[PDB]
Figure 1 (cartoon, rainbow over the protein chains, first blue to last red):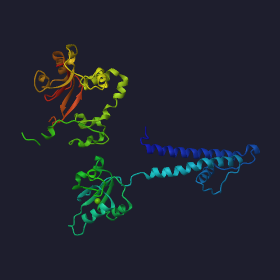
Figure 2 (tube, rainbow over the protein chains, first blue to last red):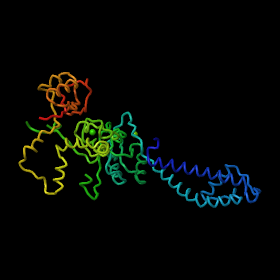
Figure 3 (cartoon, rainbow over the protein chains, first blue to last red):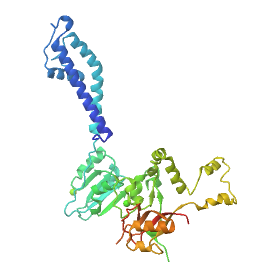
Figure 4 (cartoon, rainbow over the protein chains, first blue to last red):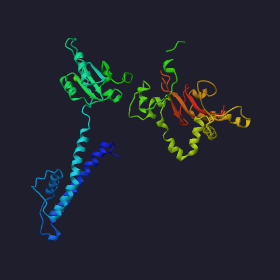
Length: 213
Length: 183
Ligand SMILES: [Ca+2]
Ligand SMILES: [Mg+2]
């Protein structure tokens, strides 16, 4: 009972079915080219290694088709025609679906490493480039007293490209984590027991302010 | 707060979503991976949710009579004759009733009793649950099915429920006993 998660089940089914179909097809082409055509008394034959067949089938799966290697037996060529009809659809659907699965993993995971003498503040609720930039422009403003408070944003979203930029420009003192204050494990990741305060921001322009409150 | 309170008010809350049980109480040590039945508010009888009922489907298959037992208790006595009368749509018909049907006013009820005072207090003073069980059944026909014990034995009014303790299980004078009784 080791594949406990539907995406991870799908990953292993994709990879193993793809690899086993590629390996078995390479073995079949290796048999056909090295044995030669039976109706030509096996005289028409071409001594490929298994590894040359394996390479050639990837080069045709992907539709690259260098033609540095190619099939020349009639059974080889008829197998390559059948392979092209089947395996272009396999490769062209496998590569996107693996890119989705490996693209799904969370970027801003992990936990706040509390320094030996810095206060920190946890900030959550409505987190966006607008709310964060107006917040940080005042909270870190040069006319305030010099105090080394760190800001820790906790929010469910992946930050947008403008907000990722702003987080990098403040890298020394602003940190961001994927999560929600609704989960005690996320409250521990940001070490909220050791924070000065939690600040909860609101979407002032929402459809329903009773729902937002 | 109340003038001559607060956390001493007895509460039970139905929850539409089981994982919200973590917000229902403090001094609690919440964990979202724990299933509802292990949580402190459920163990104290402060929470309820429909998900704990789902194995009534499987128990309804394996022993029909056990589903009728629970019903006669939880409904207080809604027999299929009442369900038929309600299915006529005329509302719940009633009036003054004959001594022949009124005999059924001696149903058995689930009750709760305290070991703090009265004849059973001798067992609350450091006796064992099996001594209490045999005594109460013999003298009173009171059949004991569990305990309701304070969690903070050393603070809060919270209590937890202990279904069917061992024969040698120690009693506390503050325990309350779940019982089946006729009066
Ligand atoms: Ca709690
Ligand atoms: Mg830091």
